[PDB]
Amino acid sequence: LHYPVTRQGEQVDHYFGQAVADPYRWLEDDRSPETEAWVKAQNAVTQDYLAQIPYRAAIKEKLAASWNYAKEGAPFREGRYHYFFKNDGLQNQNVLWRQQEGKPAEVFLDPNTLSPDGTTALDQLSFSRDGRILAYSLSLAGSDWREIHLMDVESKQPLETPLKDVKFSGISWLGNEGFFYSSYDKPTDQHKVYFHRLGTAQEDDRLVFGAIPAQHHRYVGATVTEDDRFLLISAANSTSGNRLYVKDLSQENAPLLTVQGDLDADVSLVDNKGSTLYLLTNRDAPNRRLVTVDAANPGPAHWRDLIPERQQVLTVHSGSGYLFAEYMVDATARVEQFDYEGKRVREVALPGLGSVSGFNGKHDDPALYFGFENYAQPPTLYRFEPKSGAISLYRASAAPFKPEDYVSEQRFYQSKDGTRVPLIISYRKGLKLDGSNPTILYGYGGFDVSLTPSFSVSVANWLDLGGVYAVANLRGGGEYGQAWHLAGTQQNKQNVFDDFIAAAEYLKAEGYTRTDRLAIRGGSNGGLLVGAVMTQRPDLMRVALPAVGVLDMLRYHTFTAGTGWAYDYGTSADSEAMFDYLKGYSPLHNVRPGVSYPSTMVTTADHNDRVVPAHSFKFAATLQADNAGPHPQLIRIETTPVAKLIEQSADIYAFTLYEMGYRELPR
């Protein structure tokens, strides 16, 4: 196996008088002739290696087939039509359909046509109060930038020229006058809120917040309440914590009032009832609570509990004049229904143990819809009649997978410090705990993100191939509130890696699998997780699959959206203690010459806005130069989409099973 030669530069960075060599610094430029040539060469070696795997084709074909099935989302009324997303199984992007009373359904907006190879994608859609105008954002290529298009809903033709330079933005209508959105320029790290009035040019949009020094923030958002009474402005500099402001829209030129003026807690708007604001917050409540306060004196000291904090994490949706409190019980959902006065109407019986979506609707919606799923249960839709609480099946899944053919169980293990951590293990019924089943252990562990049960075609296909899929709810995530999150941020980040290592040990000890049959996987912060564990414990697994990971913890913040993750990671510039902690686990800086790493398949796109390819490029290069054992250190750089995903999903599984010693499908 001959790796492409990777040139070593002379770059040397210094942190607190300490020197650190970075020979692959030139790879940080993913658009230079050199880097693009290296990328091309690498993909060559990789595809050549995968060519050796006989069953790859069968896996791809199995993946393709099982994916082709009709999908249809929940309907939602706007104006005089009911809209709904559909996919006949062969379409890259879901199509928005529309239908009027008794009349036949028609296509309303098909994103696939907006681009030859379906590159451009539909992100968010927002209808005016009357449903006569639709604003929707499109993401060209694969960047965080957007364009907001404006369509006349009746004729389905463009209303005005699209708004440009929109990013990390919402789209919230003030009646039928216009909408609020966010952008970094006028109308480069000072995000601002602007108001676009229909019938005017974007160059004249009025600045609402973010321009004066006191309002400078990296991220700002704006939302107008359903009844058009209040404008809520959130402002933040990092991924956790935000300030919040309110403006009464029934008054003429009302001033901004401060709901929360510090970044010591997250607080967001749920709805309003008259002049009373309903807010979800973790302020003085690690598991979050729902509070109310009068909009005319909305400070934290006046907030009053509507739904008090409990031992489980709270999330709140509103619809049909009710509030729906979703609680997380060991990563699985439970739902309760309350009225705006805080009185509990009932516990809503869910179809089982998993994840629920929905329960979101307008004040007047006669019925609410919700989806249910888990690792063995493909997405199912239900109709919930609010008043009686009657539930009825709305759309069974057309996916080619029978739930009862699988097992999905929850187990708890203990991490290094004794902490109890949940783990959900899924597989085809009939499996024996003899420790030989090929297994993929997945995790994330960060940014208060909770890994709740989710159905995946690619995963269900791994289960059919005889493999085991295990998802650990590591600290760093939000499964057990802020405490769970914080025990995995900054100088505690090692707790996340220890929890992951312990899950690996549990799976072997319980007979699910063994070291040569274990693969660990993760994406982004999960890519960091894999990179950190494979460098600290190369002896723990057979295959490592770090996707789009943050792997250079010393320079991650000098890049892209990296400037916004300091809350969770801290930066090498904060202090020497933080620099030392980061250098202590930074994957890129912990690869050592002479170590035998497991077979690795680093995945990433050639260009990416959120997590720059440089992380993966440099990590892969470093592994190829340092690895001593006979295991291949490869990198697959992606260069239509679902056809490219299936391709990549097949490449990963083929590589994994092949590296575990298989030369014929496990089953």
Image (cartoon, grey):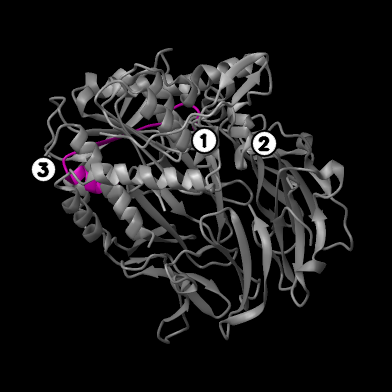
Say which element carries label 3: loop
Q: Nearer the viewer, mark 1 or mark 3?
A: 3
Q: Earlier in the sequence, mark 2 or mark 1?
A: 2
Q: What range of the chain is rendered magenta?
A: 459-477
Residue at numbered disc 3: 667
Circle 2/circle 1 CB separation < 8 Å: no
Q: Earlier in the sequence, mark 1 or mark 3?
A: 1
Tell me the CA gap for discs 2 and 1.
17 Å
Q: Residues within 10 Å of mark 2 (few under 14, many from 20)?
A: some
Q: Is residue 358 magenta?
A: no
Residue at numbered disc 2: 241
Q: Amino acid at mark 3?
A: Arg
Tell me the quadrant of the picture where the N terminus can be found: top left
Q: Is residue 447 above or below residue 581?
A: below
Q: Nearer the viewer, mark 2 or mark 3?
A: 3
Q: Is residue 471 magenta?
A: yes
- Given residues 500 and 663, the one toward you in this image is 663
| Position in image of residue 199 (x %, y %) | 76, 78
Q: Amino acid at mark 1?
A: Val
Q: Is residue 667 above or below residue 444?
A: below
108 vs 54, left or right, is right
Tell me the CA gap for discs 2 and 3.
48 Å
The tally of labels here is 3
Q: Nearer the viewer, mark 2 or mark 1?
A: 2
Q: Is residue 615 above or below residue 598?
A: below
Residue at numbered disc 1: 313
